Length: 375
Picture (cartoon, rainbow, N blue to C red):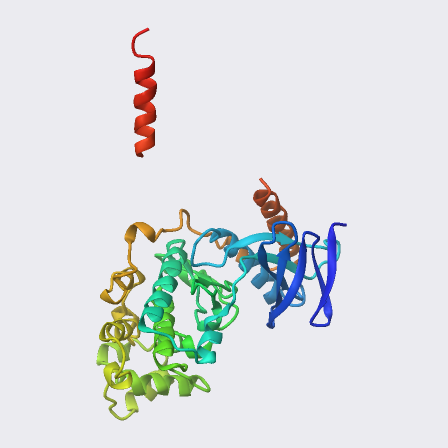
């Protein structure tokens, strides 16, 4: 066998025999997460059980998507690092185990705790999100669900993006962009307004918007645009950012929404310095640029990394791109039997994978040459 059965959340939790499951962490609608310890190395790890994978086609597409994207983004400081995967009962399996870097909690928990955060904490958190996002975007992937709950943090205040289950492709097209699939809708409070207003401009700007919402959430200690439904979400955004101009108005590619917004009473922009009077002015300037209502006016990830707010942290030589773009061909699969085969191939291929000039070079070459010059 080679595995142990633990009981967490009144279900079987079957792990690699090299580990002891120590503590339960969160449980979502897509899986349960626990902390474990490598009994030999003493190293800590998080073990995620993706649950009920073949209950709905949408759920196994989600699992396949998370599995492939976690593999593509392995090794980045600001993205949760996948270590190993396991399918304990491959004959009739309905779950997959992901072994990954162990973090302490998520950013939502830190904010919920009310513990004091400094401007330097905000800089650090925003900088780290942007570094991870630069990497993700460079592979032509949109994360689509950035929010404090999808940002893991440890005691050293290191931050890592997680949860790629809603991620979507992006392209220079037209044909390719419209073809990219989106099964789940992202979290309402952090979703860019051009989405609900049908800009048919699905760009990398949608993730920048969410980062702006996170910064605003840090600055006020509470979610900034907290709509109870989509209409209320739109009203709250408009009440802060104000009446949009005519060009932006015309970009609402939806008739009821366009006429709704057109008929509203004039609304003046509420300046962020009035909402956050104690904040760092550079924080508010970056915030204003990330929360541009119209994505065509919204700061890019690269420009944000260069913003004076982040100048202490910014080092272009330390902000890599992903070496290759990510390929979303797999999403056209609609047979759950084929999705099952694909998931097993991803796991076994990954399992074998993970089980597999400078001054010194100049002087080495010099030394070798001086050693056998003559004679």
